[PDB]
Image (tube, rainbow, N blue to C red; front, top):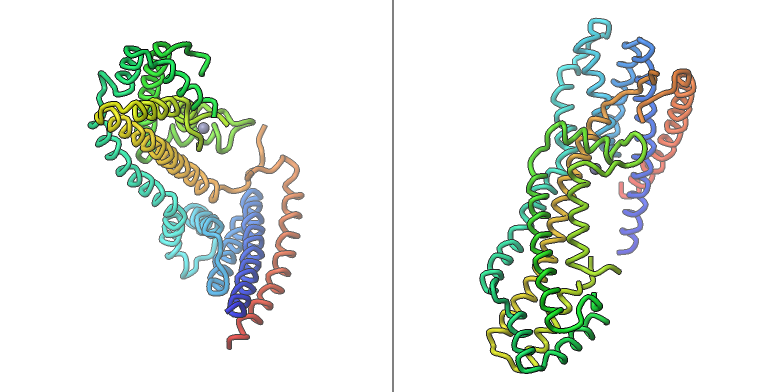
Length: 372
Ligand SMILES: [Zn+2]
């Protein structure tokens, strides 16, 4: 029913509004706490972190609180109780902080870790297909080489060249005759095979939880660069190889067929028209299945590359979530004399979010009370 759908839609939109207003409130409280630590007053900051955790717990039923904001409060409160103690009063909640932080980190990382596992597993069926298909194709004397050869022999090569050219116009200037096509296709197949070996090796060498030199290199390269993105990290270098292989597996202006595959399709079409031995047609058909498998493998290899890249991005997101506001010395950075300007902006942000949250929770309570 569209009415139960309407009530659900109004409740979801309203709940999201409560969630955003609470996110803005908690964000302002954490910022104000970060200033108190910069000033030196560790106790006043601890009260704000404790309020962040208290408010999130109170509203956990009605709305969700960003795990990173809760982790920001939990971790920085733990930092004060491990070192700055006994300046901060103890509470019966202090013992739970370590496990809560670990749970928040685990919950946040769960998606990117599952996506690494799923992207890795997704590659096995297509790779087994590629191994099965390559067993059925002759490497030394391929079907298309023997089709070209017999076409030149019986002087039906002109019809073949015209049929290959018509399929392209639907690097044709790179070959004049059938022998020119033969050598051009040899080079293009060798190039594809070299592109495949390299892209697979590039992916293989990005697997596994990466080292600190890799995390930091990717961060200064494309996550948080000093100015413009560097495009020099192991992931960016691998993507340059993917682009190179894509330009040969597909055509420019990943969906449209390459000129190599188009030529191969036309040679197979010519072989069928001229009623060549079933062996040539079968091998040609297997080559078409192989081009299909290579395109599927490309997409799955790039998704696996993406999953591994995203895991590095997520680890940086975790590190940045716990990072506090620090006054710049000659993001979480404040100018030498903008400390008061930041405090004022945060105090007004808290005031507006407190007001918006009260209004939105009242409307949410109304929508909830219709079902009784
Ligand atoms: Zn990079």
